[PDB]
Structure formats: structure tokens, C-alpha cells
Length: 22
Image (cartoon, rainbow, N blue to C red; front, side, top):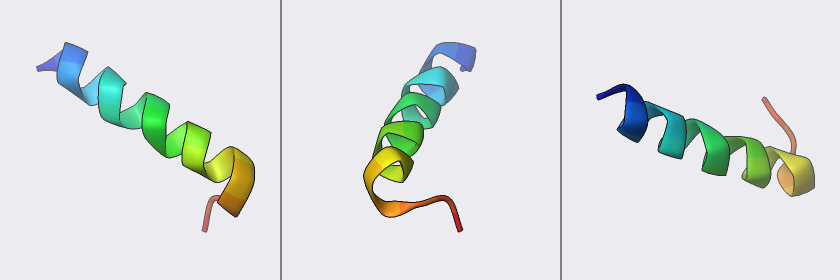
């Protein structure tokens, strides 16, 4: 499920670009 993991990681990183990574 590496493809699905990469999808979630991409959107988490996008969220972090506006809201931080905490």
C-alpha cells in the first residue's frame, strides 16, 4: 500500500505548508 501511503503523506505535507508540522 506504498501508493496509498504516499498519497496521505503528500496531503499531510501540503497541510503543513499552511498549518505547521507539530
